[PDB]
Amino acid sequence: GDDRELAILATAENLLEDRPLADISVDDLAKGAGISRPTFYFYFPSKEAVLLTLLDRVVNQADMALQTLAENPADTDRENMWRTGINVFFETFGSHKAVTRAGQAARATSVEVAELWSTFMQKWIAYTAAVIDAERDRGAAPRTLPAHELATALNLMNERTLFASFAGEQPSVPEARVLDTLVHIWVTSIYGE
Amino acid sequence: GDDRELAILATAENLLEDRPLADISVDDLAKGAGISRPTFYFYFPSKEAVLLTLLDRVVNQADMALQTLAENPADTDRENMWRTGINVFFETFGSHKAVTRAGQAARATSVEVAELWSTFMQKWIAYTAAVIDAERDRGAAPRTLPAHELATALNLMNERTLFASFAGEQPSVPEARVLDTLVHIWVTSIYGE
């Protein structure tokens, strides 16, 4: 049961590296998973439902990693704290580039994908704003912009910039430079007067 | 000739406010422009070609406004200089929200739209980087990140943030707060050590 589902998911991720979801058929997915067409429809109603499940897995992996980081005290200087956090997203989504690219393209056509992404971005922005607030309370960061508004723009920057880098878009920051670039902008805008 | 084309374009922009391009038919466009179906095909090969022409108009309007601003000496304090520039994009794209939304959604499915957007983003990023470089040369800004990489991330932030605000996405910065938010992040990251 769970073995056949995991085989469909693994097949979809593999095929999405080579081509978009439009050019992948349900016949391709069943064949790669070693099952028949009707057996595929037992596990998933459509190929779009397969992508949604892959995205849910990737987004929860990133969220759980961020939770682990937040639960520990660990935090050297302020710059390293932010770098370690942004790196969770750099490494998680960067290890699943095909799923990431397909998920962004599906946001325009799928309310389910849009809603999944929205839910997690809200969570991540709220956490960012809470850390900024704590820095302001302890006297480390100045009271400039509304923290939630600052957090929103910085997280939207990270979304667009990380995903442009992974997809090799023009324009984009090179993948090997994107962490330094983002961390600079976060630290200067959070601690700068 | 030019009158019938302008009527098709005006009709498309009007209908895109109410519904996406998928739910607009060529029959809808011809009817609104006061022409027949075959007459429509004389001016445009498809409804997708109509959207491309609308986007080209909007993007060139923004580019020409930025050129006008750049050609004059005018530049009070450093903060106001950047604000006046970002405002060109805030006002231009914000005055054509339907075209803007449809254009972003079409980037995933249309190489022509992707290429148009890429061309202008390259131009705008290059200009940003040139101004940062001039600020560093005169001793006003510190030599921190590579200017072109900083310019790329800041422009990608503006793209994603402005368009989320116009579309009323969750999450997003409120439209009435987005200029202040972006300007803060630009000024702190450009002039901050």
Image (cartoon, coloured by chain):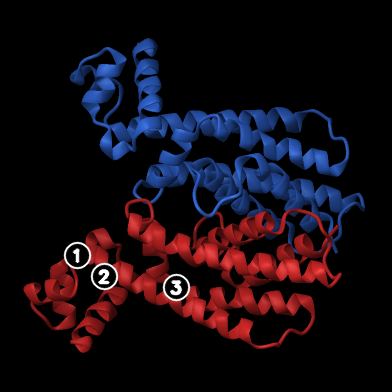
Chain colours: A red, B blue
How far separated are the C-alphas under marks 1 and 3?
A: 20 Å
x and y percentages locating residue A140 in the rendered image:
84, 70
Check the image and report above or below for B41 versus B144.
above
Identity of the residue drawn at 88% across and 52% down: B137
Secondary structure state at the residue bearing disc 1? loop
Quadrant containing the N terminus of chain B is: top left
Secondary structure state at the residue bearing disc 2? helix
Q: Is residue B2 left or right of residue B137?
A: left
Q: Nearer the viewer, residue B137 or A130?
A: A130
Check the image and report above or below for A117 versus A145.
below
- Which residue position holds label 3? A59
Q: Amino acid at mark 2?
A: Val
Q: Earlier in the sequence, mark 1 or mark 3?
A: 1
Q: Residue lying furthest front in this view?
A: A137
Callout 1 touching callout 3 (CB < 8 Å): no
Q: Report if residue A18 is visible in the image.
A: no
x and y percentages locating residue B18 in the rendered image:
36, 31
Q: Report if residue B149 is visible in the image.
A: yes
Identity of the residue drawn at 19% across and 20% down: B38
Q: Earlier in the sequence, mark 2 or mark 3?
A: 2
- Which residue position holds label 2? A50
- Which residue position holds label 1? A46
- Dot 1 and dot 3 within a common chain: yes
Q: Nearer the viewer, residue B129 or B184?
A: B184
